[PDB]
Length: 255
Image (cartoon, rainbow, N blue to C red; front, side, top):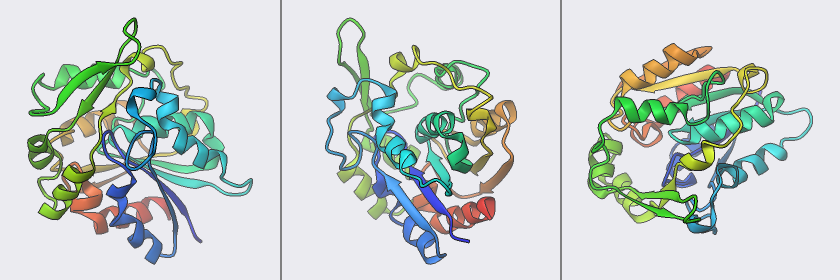
């Protein structure tokens, strides 16, 4: 039976990361929507006009709003894409057969939206992002924070198991992004009733140097998932370093 995978990229990246995974899932007979979130990929918005996490996630929500009455989707969220999964799961829990997180913080409906970030930024050193750079933007009375990935950070910490071509593509395509911390600090947390009704799966990427496996495991341990798979030699960009494995894990989880 044909599944519809909605793939959601992490911060500063775009739908294009899925360019290897998407045709694989399609050759398996499945439908795939790879979404650019707002001001990501070639989405035509600018980051300095995106101030809320809901606005950032809107292209995903639009895909969710368009799932027909008798269909569901399988979501796959990479990295920060996992937060947009949570929003999709809180909003349209009945529309999702399983929400798959990969190298992603899985929201915990027991805690605030910022909790996984508060956690990340307690367990991880302050210089972890190397040559990446941050700057504020938006309302001076309540500024957003944007970031740009450094090419050493990308090379060493995100794409180190990927081809040079994929890293090249990332250097050519990465755009400023934001984690919307201060907007997330004022959201409405997800609920166990809604977000928590949705089957969760985790795909571990064991060589992820950006979101290390021990931290992936901590999210799975503390939050829980119904299915877990591991890709031993996936880096942070498992859909580019190990697209076939991601495709097998996904079909496994979904079928």
